[PDB]
Amino acid sequence: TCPFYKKIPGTGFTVDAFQYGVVEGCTAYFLTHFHSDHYAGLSKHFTFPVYCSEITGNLLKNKLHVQEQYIHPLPLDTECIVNGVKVVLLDANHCPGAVMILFYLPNGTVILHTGDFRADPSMERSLLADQKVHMLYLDTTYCSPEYTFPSQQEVIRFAINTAFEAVTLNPHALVVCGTYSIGKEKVFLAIADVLGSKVGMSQEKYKTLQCLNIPEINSLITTDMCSSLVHLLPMMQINFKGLQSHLKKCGGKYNQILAFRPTGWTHSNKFTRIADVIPQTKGNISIYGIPYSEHSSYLEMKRFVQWLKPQKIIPTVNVGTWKSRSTMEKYFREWKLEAGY
Ligand code: NI
Image 1: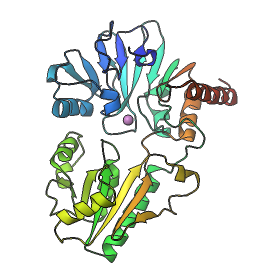
Image 2 (image 1 turned 180 degrees about the vertical axis):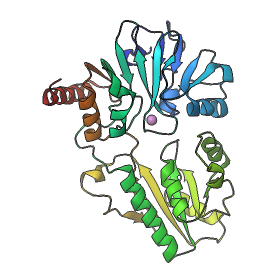
Image 3 (image 1 turned 90 degrees about the vertical axis):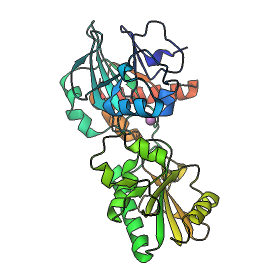
């Protein structure tokens, strides 16, 4: 049964709740972004409205094959009416097409649902700047002060430099990047751009990227592997046995892979900086981990919530145990007491 934190009070609206069957009372199903935990359940056989971003729309039509009529895309940053409820979609700074949703209730309550987000000061000069928000449904993925990680721009700097070094030292080395969903496209695109290449990938990954309205994308990617010295692979495949295997297939065209695993937080964030990163090495293959996050750090989250001063906070992540629930509330109280709301 759909949990209470996936429902919006005083509406027939639900948020990312596609995996329970029909939810009695729901007139409309919002989808925040195209990631399989959030969309789990959709198919070609859905005949209720889905509201989402244009980009999420394209992925629903082209990857899951939902029928064009039931996909209602909405522009961002635009006051829109949806069954006589004002809603706005805002960029969530997560993966491509990912949104937060502002709900303006009939009664006068205003609710913000973040979806998955990486909180940023640019959001403090958006449409949220204009009015009071009473309820916040919050992405709590990293709600604990251990969770620090660098800025995305720091990581992209590191990556660009590493790859450009090696390729210039050894012109027969291949760059590889791991992936399993949308998001983190800037990693492979920034690398490929510094190296004067297109990114090569499988047919299904090419199809996925062609839905994202990336500008000039036809110049940036290809399905021709031979012609490309930055390749993408399944994240499962990014290891020695799988990279060896793949290094065979290229047929004596490269003598060294230099791979990147963009990951989230790992425990090596607690003791090591980004400028002082190393890879594992089994011969001619060297695998970098790089903590490129598309979720709020503890401090970024803190700052956003303390600016917003919401009257009530409802967590959407790590709610499955009482210990996590209890721990999170403690931080919510400290924030509110420090800030005086
Ligand atoms: Ni996500």
